[PDB]
Amino acid sequence: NPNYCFAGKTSSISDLKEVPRKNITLIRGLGAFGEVYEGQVPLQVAVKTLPEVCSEQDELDFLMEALIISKFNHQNIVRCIGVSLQSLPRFILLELMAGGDLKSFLRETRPRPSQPSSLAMLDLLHVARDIACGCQYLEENHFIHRDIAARNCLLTCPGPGRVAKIADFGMARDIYRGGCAMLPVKWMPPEAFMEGIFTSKTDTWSFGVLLWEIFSLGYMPYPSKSNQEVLEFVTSGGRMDPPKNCPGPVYRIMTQCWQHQPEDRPNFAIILERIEYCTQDPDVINTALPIEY
Ligand SMILES: C[C@@H](Oc1cc(-c2cnn(C3CCNCC3)c2)cnc1N)c1c(Cl)ccc(F)c1Cl
View (cartoon, rainbow, N blue to C red):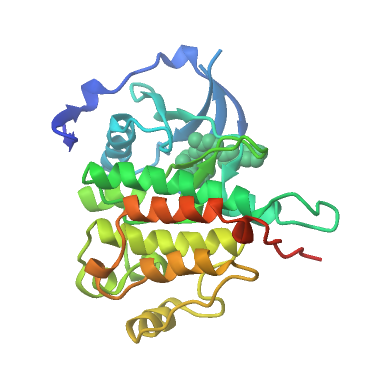
């Protein structure tokens, strides 16, 4: 059986907390490859399933993601409650994040004439800070995520006390051991999509794109551009414009994350400091978000 190494020590399937299948109840679906359910073990969980019709490589991928998530310990990375791998279909049990994924949340919670104050700049800055703290933890533990993006982040709840967390680690799992059209090229720096070079500064660039996602309130990056068009755009020095109403200090964090040379981009300690300074600036947090009519 395959092993996984993180933060010093090695782990195996035997290290995963196997939860008796009889102790697990599925409640409802929550919406690719394999289904997700709300469940109970009482402890409320999200249940990620492996389809019984799958390849041996699918099985190993599933095992590896379980090992990866179970080995993290940080408040801004989703918790793994355990697994149920000894019954079929196989389960991974995660912290239930009632707020759902960040991209969907931003789109469905955009300020509206019905909900004029559904969200403010400070809410967005807090989400950005949460994920940046998660990224800093990964960076200081030498883990490269490779796919930092709104679709891969979850929220504990829709309301004001919400906390954002990095939740999907499928790309990192694949590389740890696919095709061009499935690569998240719109979140990738030049050296990543050209040379296949990944470092912590890969995630910095991706975080810049996430920031754009956040302050655009859930738009797809590089509006109207295809993957190849973005590849050529970014390679030639092109960068996204500020999202609608985006404060200049926030846009500046994005453009620093998108420096062409990785050495010129900030690490996550610096990004955190700059996000913190934005949260302090009245001219930033007093800026009204656009109201979608
Ligand atoms: C694997 C799956 O896990 C969860 C999904 C959800 C989830 C998805 N959608 N919703 C909605 C349920 C109805 N109310 C709004 C949120 C909750 C909550 N916690 C989870 N651990 C998941 C999904 Cl589905 C999407 C992105 C992710 F990063 C992850 Cl990690």
